[PDB]
Amino acid sequence: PLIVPYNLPLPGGVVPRMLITILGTVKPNANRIALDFQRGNDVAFHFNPRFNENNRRVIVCNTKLDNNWGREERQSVFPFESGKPFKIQVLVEPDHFKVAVNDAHLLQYNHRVKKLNEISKLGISGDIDLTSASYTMI
Ligand SMILES: Cn1nc([C@@H]2O[C@H](CO)[C@H](O)[C@H](n3cc(-c4ccc(Br)c(F)c4F)nn3)[C@H]2O)n(-c2cc(Cl)ccc2C(F)(F)F)c1=S
Ligand SMILES: [Mg+2]
Image (cartoon, rainbow, N blue to C red; front, side, top):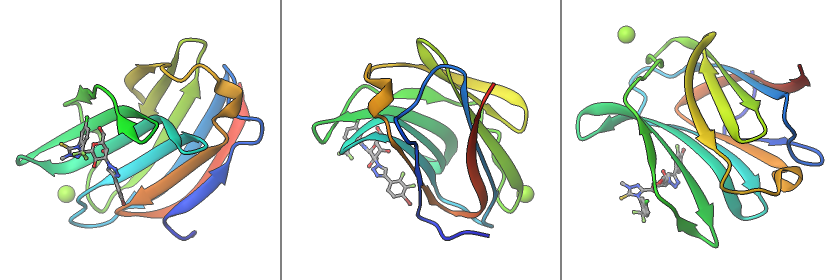
């Protein structure tokens, strides 16, 4: 039981084989969730499940550089459900972030931001109740 928006410091940034686990419960009638892996003001990886974009559920991923959003990467496979407990796992790999939700693989997002050791904050926000936010090395 933690407050949303929540900031999780990633001391010294991220590194391959670093696994970030976020546990929580989606609120009933949710509109959006966002995970923002930040390098200062830039967003190295924005993971954004949208429950109602043109009456469809979509996961939108992007990068924000110098306050400009890049080319979006979209995924129609949508494992979240309003009112349900979830687990999101972000596994930092050499060339991409690998995302798995509720122990099932979801997507990969290739690194556009290369200074991994400077992505030192994960912002967690949106239509959820947050239970815990932590990391370990596998
Ligand atoms: C309908 N739409 N939405 C976007 C932006 O698309 C981005 C990904 O490409 C981010 O999702 C961004 N966004 C979302 C939030 C956000 C906040 C609060 C919570 Br709580 C939370 F969950 C959150 F997602 N803050 N910024 C969002 O505003 N764009 C978009 C897309 C691109 Cl490529 C470039 C520019 C834009 C923009 F200028 F129009 F914004 C459109 S078009
Ligand atoms: Mg339902």
